[PDB]
Image: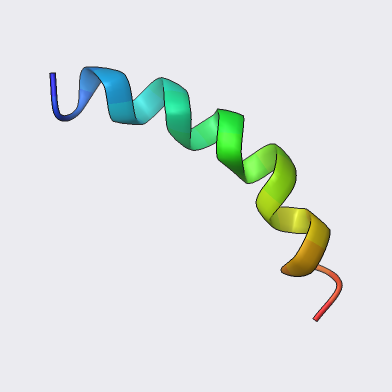
Length: 24
């Protein structure tokens, strides 16, 4: 599931991406 395993992982990463994203 290129989308099934991506939708979940997405939010899982977004929680960390904000570390450098929202920062920069």
